[PDB]
Each structure stands twice: as structure tokens, then as C-alpha cells.
Amino acid sequence: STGSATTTPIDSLDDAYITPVQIGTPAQTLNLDFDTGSSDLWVFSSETTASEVDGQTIYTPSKSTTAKLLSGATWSISYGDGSSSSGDVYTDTVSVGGLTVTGQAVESAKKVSSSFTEDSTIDGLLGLAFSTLNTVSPTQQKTFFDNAKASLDSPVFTADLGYHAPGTYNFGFIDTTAYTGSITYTAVSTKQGFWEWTSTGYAVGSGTFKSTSIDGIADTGTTLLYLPATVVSAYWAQVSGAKSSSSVGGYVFPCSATLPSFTFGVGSARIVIPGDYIDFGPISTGSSSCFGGIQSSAGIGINIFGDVALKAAFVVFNGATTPTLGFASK
């Protein structure tokens, strides 16, 4: 089997992407944030505290004839951005772009943190990291991909995120029309439950390539590119007027400035992030100060190849017995 679904930016800055997901019988369609940096499929629901729901579409398990309580199961998650959610668990039928999993754990939120409430466009998350990170207790649950894997034509999914435009998540096949050149595959460590890999270096604009190992995660659920402070400083030093603002919480730059591209290494191959992808607009409405899309990972504890990086490539998440990651230009 295979599946193919369009993913759509939530706003004009590509702050996140939402993909429609069918849950239950008859189908309830929710727009979920596909997150290769986590491993829970959780949704706003009829059980979510009413004051914490503000425009989201909810899953109502009582209206699904295939929903079954996962008795005794609870879940609770906190994300790198400080947001969180928790609740109980049902199993139900979940379909993405034509691909159907029966008995998928659907984690129903009883509580969500303010950032989730305040974002009306995201109805939940669909985790695509390794199932070892799943928070369901007492019995850890499998991700949608893990459940589908054995049935897929090939045990892979791909992320093809658009710049200020829709893109595509495919399951079970590689669309050879969706990228240019070849796909370069690189080793993955699953030791932290992430799609963790090592970039071979970077360049800033037309500058020479610096060969240096950068361990980080391929994370579709993180908006920006977070790299070591040395790398980030080298980038922003090439932008007139850029500075790190402690009050704002990262590098900002005048929108009159021209942003250089940023290249990262995948083996001997190179992915070029165009300068425009690194502009995240005014820090506040009407401000001449713009927020940068490359920021320091110092104090996160890990480097994150988030959407800024991933949307510059066609990315293969290869879930073979020894997982690997593939990157192609497009």
C-alpha cells in the first residue's frame, strides 16, 4: 500500500504545516501537524477542557463506531517549545492520503497548553519519530508509520515541504518526479528516538564550504533551523545590521537587508537554503526588525534541522531495519 497527502502552511510565514487526517467511522477529518520530532498522535477532542478549545476541530470518539477505549491508558507530553498536552487514549481507524491503519492509538487531549489553544489551525499532532518516544502509559503505543510499515510497498515516508506553498507527505514510495539529481542517504542514530544524523558541514552564501560534523535531528515539527552558536554567528555576520537580541530571543535583522543562502552538507552532497527561506518577518506588526530563520541551538541540547532546512530538500525517512535519511535537491 501507499498514501499521499498534501501538507499546507498554517500562515504566510510557514510557521507550521497541517495535513488532513481521517479518524474514525464515519471519518472525522482533523488537520494535524506531522512531527518527525515526536511520537504521539494526539487530537483536540470532545474531552478537551472547554475553555482550552478555540476554533479547533475536535475528534468525538463516541460518534465513531470503530473507536475503542484503551482502558487505563494515559499520555502526557511536553515539547521543546515549552508547550504540553495530556489525556486518555482510544484506538481507531486512521487514514492519511488513502493509507489506512486500523487500531491506531489516538490520544485524546483532556488538557492542552495555551499555545495550542491559541493556534486555531492545528487540531493535533501526528508523530513520526521512533515509537520509543511515545508517552502512552502503561503500554507504549506505535506511531502511524510504525503501524503502517509492514503493509507499505517500501518501509519509507517522504517529506516535501513547500516554501510559502503546499507540499506533500508520501508513505510507502519515493516519487522520482519530485526532486532533481540523486538522493544522498546518510546514517541515522535512533538512540534518542529521533531521526538523528550528522551533517558534513556548511557554507554561507557564496562562501567556501566548512567541513565540520554537525549532529542534529530532522524535525518537521520545528519551524526554524537551530545550529551551534559558532555556525549561526558566521551566518548573521554576513547580514548588514543583524544582531542577537536577548529581549526578542534570537537574531533579528533589518528587512532592507539581503539574506545570503545557507548550504548544509549531506555526505558529499549539498542542500542550499535560499536566503528568502530565512526571513520570518517583522518581530511585531509594523516593526522594521525581522526575525531570523537560523538561530542558535545553545541550551536546547541538540541541533534541529527544522522546516527552514527541510523545505529546501526532498527528504526520505527510511524505516528499513537500519533506518537512514535521504536528502535530494528539488
Image (cartoon, helix red, strand yellow):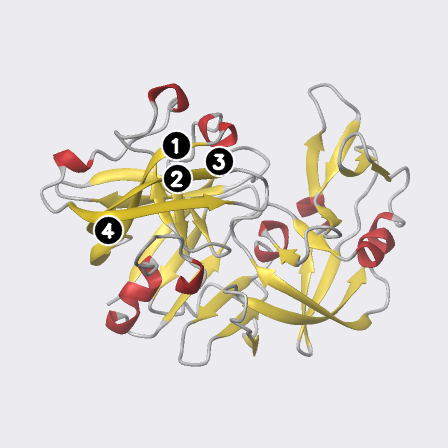
Identify which residue is drawn at 55% across, 56% down: 219
Residue 111, disc:
1
Of helix, strand and loop, which one carries label 2?
strand
> How many numbered circles are shown?
4
- Dot 4 or dot 2: first in sequence order is 2
Helix, strand or loop at label 1? It is strand
Callout 3–callout 1 Cβ contact below 8 Å: no
Q: Quadrant of residue 249?
A: top right
Which of the two residues, 272 or 110, is positioned nearer the viewer here? 110
Report the mark closest to the observer, 4 or 1.
1
Mark sitting earlier along the chain (4/3): 3
Is any atom of residue 72 visible in this view? yes
Q: CA distance from mark 3 to mark 1?
A: 22 Å
Q: Amino acid at mark 2?
A: Ser
Measured as percent of width and height from the top left, residue 141 is found at 32, 58
Disc assigned to residue 195? none
Q: Nearer the viewer, mark 4 or mark 3?
A: 4
Residue drawn at x 33%, y 68% as measured from the top left: 172
Closer to the camera in the image, 128 or 284: 128
Q: Which amino acid does the dot numbered 1 rest on?
A: Lys
